[PDB]
Length: 223
Ligand SMILES: [Ca+2]
Image (tube, rainbow, N blue to C red; front, side, top):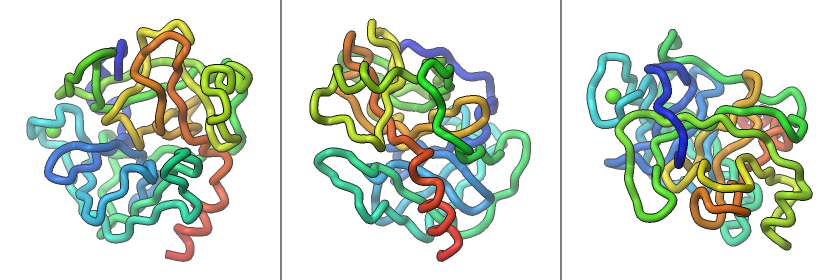
C-alpha cells in the first residue's frame, strides 16, 4: 500500500496473508474455512495466516492454516487478468473471534463514488521496493468506469473496476495482490493489477467481486 496508513492492530480481521515461506499475496476470509484471493496468486502449496498485524513478529493472535483446495476461476486469463479470482479451502476451520472474523460478500455492485478500505502488506513505495512489517490501510473511492477505461484503453473488462486516485500518490501495489477492497462491510474488489504503483492517471485495477457471488457460493457448496 503506497501512501496509506498503519491499520490499528486487528482492525481488519478478515485480512489474511498467503505464505509460501514468505508473504506473497493477501486475501479475505469469507467463512470459517474459505478465503477468496486472486488467481494470479496461485501456488501448489500455500499456508494461510490469520490474525496478523506484524507479519514478522509473533504477537499471540495468529492462526496458521494450510490450504487444502486451491481453486482458480476456470476462465482466468493470465494475459489480461480477466476473472482474476481464486478460492482457497483451508484444511480445517479457524477459530472465529475479534482478530479473526469473516467479511461479507456483495449484495450488489457498489456505485462509483463509494469510499472503500484497501489493506495489505505489499510494497509501500511508488518507485523501488519496501515491504512493511505492519498491515497498511488505505481509504480510496471507487472510480467511474469511464475513467478506468480511459486510463487503460482496451484492457478494462466488465469484471474489473478501478479504485483509487487519478492524481497518484496513494494506491495498492505488488504484494497487496489478492487482498480486499471492502466498502460498507462488503467485499467489492480484489487487488489485481495496474501500471506501476501510485502513478498519476494510472489507478489500481481490481476484480469486480459482485460479478462472482454465484460462482463463489456454487464452488463452496460443490467442494
Ligand atoms: Ca504476527
